[PDB]
Structure formats: structure tokens, C-alpha cells
Image (cartoon, rainbow over the protein chains, first blue to last red):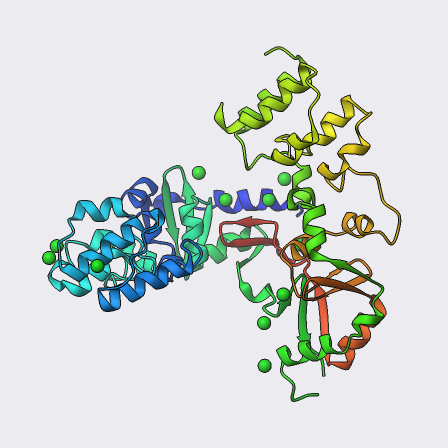
Amino acid sequence: NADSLPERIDLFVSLFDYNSATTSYDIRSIQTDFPTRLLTPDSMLPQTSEYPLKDIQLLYKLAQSCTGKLPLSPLITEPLVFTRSLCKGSSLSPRWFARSGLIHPGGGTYAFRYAEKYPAQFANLLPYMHIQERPNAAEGTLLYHLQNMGEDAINALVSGASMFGSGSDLWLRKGDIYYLFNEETWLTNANKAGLSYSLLSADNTCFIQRGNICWDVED
Amino acid sequence: SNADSLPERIDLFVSLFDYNSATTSYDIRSIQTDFPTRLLTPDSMLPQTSEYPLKDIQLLYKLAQSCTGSPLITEPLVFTRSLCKGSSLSPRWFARSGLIHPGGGTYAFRYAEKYPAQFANLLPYMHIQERPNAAEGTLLYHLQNMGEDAINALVSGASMFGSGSDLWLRKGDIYYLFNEETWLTNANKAGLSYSLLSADNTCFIQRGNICWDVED
Ligand SMILES: [Cl-]
Ligand SMILES: [Cl-]
Ligand SMILES: [Cl-]
Ligand SMILES: [Cl-]
Ligand SMILES: [Cl-]
Ligand SMILES: [Cl-]
Ligand SMILES: [Cl-]
Ligand SMILES: [Cl-]
Ligand SMILES: [Cl-]
Ligand SMILES: [Cl-]
Ligand SMILES: [Cl-]
């Protein structure tokens, strides 16, 4: 038959039984237990687009020697407080980690770096660490699915998309609940609705780009 | 040659051009002063729905009709009441304001539609799409025929970009324009194939990270 592409997507969604899902998660529970900065993969990388590079460099060299020039910019206030606390050896309460901003300018979280110096505090500071910094969770748990999510799946989850795919699981949103279905159900209902799909891939993007010109070899 | 890498072939491609044999040349430092970025980007002609609350955009449109009637709208609220109360504005106010009106376009274009006398003296503060179509060969003609990608490449000062039938090559502070045949000839000499950034592969039926399509 001939149903419109938006109508075939709605038909695809209506074929699912939300009570037959593998598991389900409440969006509000995810937002409460996992701040966005602890899910996005870019938080693990140096924050070279947030801070001036000189301040990241001044902070790095200050941490290596615990002496020298202090970056006193207001943007680097909390990273400076964290850096000088590790040097002298003063303690940082869990309340400080809750308001500090979580993410260190060099990549990663304050809590993980603090736990590397004080290993006994690792368990108590886990709620303030990036999901990639926490131990590998057991299969079937929420943290397991989050740790195996690519950047596209994370952004779709954070933005509350109607649906997204992560590995072999299809996530469907209805209200404040995400319902997970396996690959076989995803393929079956997409085939019943006369639909084909592909995940968002960088294979379309050209990586040899000058201005608005994509270059390629041609012998 | 065949042993040249893809970045090496691009350098060979650029070296094949005679910068003295260019069709025309423009100075970047002069383009930046004569044309602010907000007057070149095509999205400035559209309503600034990503910069102001939509309720605050409609209320600005309601007051513009019936001239009776916060801090995020401090500057455009001055313009709307100046338009209503007939307070003729100065060009120094345009060069100091944000130029772009929240409902799309520029302040100088809306101010020149009520007062069509100072229209010629307010062109440097209007968008290139609002100015009349320039004649071929002029700088404004090339700018008015640039797509969204060519505009961003020019503003970013890219090493090169293509716009229509011209190839723009940057050598320091000067952009040199070459014809389509010269572009295609030197690319073939360097063993290169090229294409413009296109949205023909961009997926517009997207739900999350899933791109949907009709099964054939
Ligand atoms: Cl439809
Ligand atoms: Cl110190
Ligand atoms: Cl301690
Ligand atoms: Cl502690
Ligand atoms: Cl969606
Ligand atoms: Cl929903
Ligand atoms: Cl490259
Ligand atoms: Cl190379
Ligand atoms: Cl470039
Ligand atoms: Cl398309
Ligand atoms: Cl759509």
C-alpha cells in the first residue's frame, strides 16, 4: 500500500506493546541520578572550547609542580580551588562536588581525580563521576546501557527524543518512561510498517574539507 | 603524482594557480569592515526565534501595528517606540546597535521603509539581501549570490571555498577568484576530485539517532 512516511512511523510505534518491553526507565529518575555533564562523552576530553588554552595550561603546570603563577580568572575559580586543594592536601566535601561544576578543565570529573589521590573516597564520590569513569556495570542495569551508548544515543536520550537506538536495543518514549525493545521486535515492526532505517552515521560526512569543498583522490 | 597524499595533492592544487592571472581580488580586512557578519549570514533575514522568547517577538509585532501598547528586548524596544514616536534615528545609533531586528531583517531597512529619504545613506547598515541587486563584477553581486555555506566559509576566512562559477582562494589577506574551468583543470592536474557541501545526503526524516525511509 501507500501510507505517508510520517504515518508509517506512527504505525511502527503503535505496533509495540509497552507492557512487553525488556525493561523501562523513568526519565525523571535518570535526570536526578545522572546529570547531563556526567553522560556526554565530551566531558572526558579537555575542555578546550570552554576555557582559554592558556588557563588550562597554567592550571596543568600548577598541578604538576604545586607552585608558580595562579590563573585568577573568574571562569577558572573552581578549577583553581580544586587544584590548590590537592596540592596542600585539604579535603573537599561531597557538598563541594555537588556545586563545583563536576567537570575538570583537563577532561574528566573532579571526583574521579580526587579519588585517584584518595582511593578510599572512591565509593562515596561515585555519584559525582562520569559514567565512563565508574566501574563497568553488570549487564541489564541502567548504568550498563548508559556506558555502552554512543554520543548520538546519549544526546537523543538527554533531549528526550521520541525514540533512539543503542546497539541492539530500541528505546521508545511515551510520557516520562522509556521502553526498551530488542532487535527482533525492532526489525519485525519496521518490516510490518514498510519501513527501513539506518542509524545516524558519520560515513556520510567528508573529512577532507576546505571551506565548503570536499576533496578526494582521483588517479 | 600517485605517491602524493590527499593533503599533498591539495597543496599541489593550490600551487598551480597564478595569483596574478586572477579574475578579481578582494581584501579580507576591507570586507570585514564594510560588511559585518550579521549583515551577511542568511539566517539574519529570518525571525530570531532562537535569540528571543516567542511571546516577546509577537508583542513586538503587536506594538509595531497599533503604536500604543523587559531587559532582553531593551535595544529593539527602543527602536519600535522610536519608529512610533517619529524619533528620527542617526547612523551612529545603527552602527552601535545590534543591527538585526528580532523579527528578521535589520533596523535600518525597517527604518528606511517609513522614511524612504535616508535609504541611500543607511545601506551600510542593512543586510545584503535587503539592498538592491548589484551589477555583475561587483563585490556585492558575489556576496548576494553566495549560499549559506559560502558565507560561513568567507566569514571564517577559509583557505578556499566555491560560490557559483567562482573559486575563492585565500593567500594571506587577499581572496583571489578563479573561473570554473581553471578550478576543474588544476584539480585534474593534481589528481583530485571535489564536490560542494550538499544537503542531498542529509537525512530529514530523523527521530533521535534513527533515520527513517520507505522500504522499497
Ligand atoms: Cl502524513
Ligand atoms: Cl599554590
Ligand atoms: Cl582528605
Ligand atoms: Cl575526602
Ligand atoms: Cl523525536
Ligand atoms: Cl512522549
Ligand atoms: Cl584534512
Ligand atoms: Cl601528507
Ligand atoms: Cl580551510
Ligand atoms: Cl535528503
Ligand atoms: Cl519529519
